Image 1 (cartoon, chains in turn red, blue):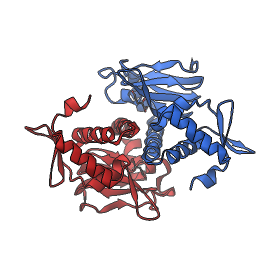
Image 2 (cartoon, helix red, strand yellow):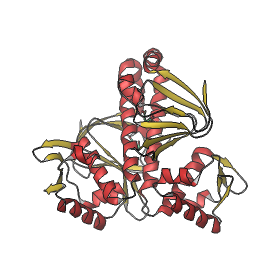
Image 3 (cartoon, rainbow over the protein chains, first blue to last red):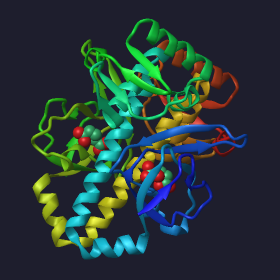
Image 4 (spheres, chains in turn green, orange):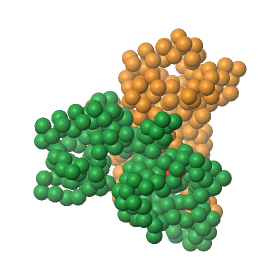
Length: 196
Length: 196
Ligand SMILES: O=C(O)CCC(=O)C(=O)O
Ligand SMILES: O=C(O)CCC(=O)C(=O)O
């Protein structure tokens, strides 16, 4: 069981795709990185996700092109591909469960496609927040607290927007009392009604 | 082998998720259908993709929420979920090959997250076409031909835009001599350079 301090890198673009990973605790951010250091978020992975799947294809013969970061303190398992490939070719059942895990990854990414497809950033934001509710939400008298520290920057990198825009949108959502924010934990007040 | 005419439905929202599918020839469109009747594209699957993967999660106890349509004339295989779990037992190797196809689906979806992430609708379109060039590309004296009838509406539904805007953007690109269109098939003239 490995641990990663918050903001520690799990793999860098350019690193051989040596291992597969399983996320026990915390959130992992996958992103694409650009020459100047800008990053675009491509996935925010929730507990119990398999990831690093490019090694399931090319194994260490190929290089990472996304950046994997411990978005919160993380705990995870990982194993070179042949170790995995052995464990599978050996334990048939296990594979049925990784097939399920991968199927989940795909359905989750497609939900982000849906979030990103909205033309107006306001809905893009609510929709992204509703997903986080589901992935990391904690029940509350108000509604649901997204148990992650979310900077305006981090949100911008994930819904395709600038930070200034996120700030304005977030302020608008509070003015209207659909959300509260405290030390970066966002609480969504009426999740179910927001899925309108 | 099951064939489907262009624009025929392979599976509708509400259907039991009982089968896994394999795409042999053509392109399959996955969408979310909305209350009104508008449709948002979540994936354009290319030949040799596994899909319907919701059925490897629950199976019957779960109803399709996406719409699977033959975007071009299509041929595919399919099987009841419990038959898949069986051949998985039989051939612990076939297993790995599913794992790998699922891995590739994940990566393909993430690459669409990147497309949608662009703020500049022009760039988002160029990026969507590059995808199409590698997914449905055919080498050309002129560069790479995307082998698909693409209406502006269809492009709009996949890049979170509208017909009108797509028409303007395609024309801009054509003025720059950057793409060509014949019979609704688009040719991208220097895709390797554009990748910039
Ligand atoms: O596997 C990689 O190299 C990038 C994408 C990824 O980590 C996955 O979503 O599992
Ligand atoms: O499995 C479905 O029901 C929806 C998503 C899907 O078809 C997949 O991308 O393979």
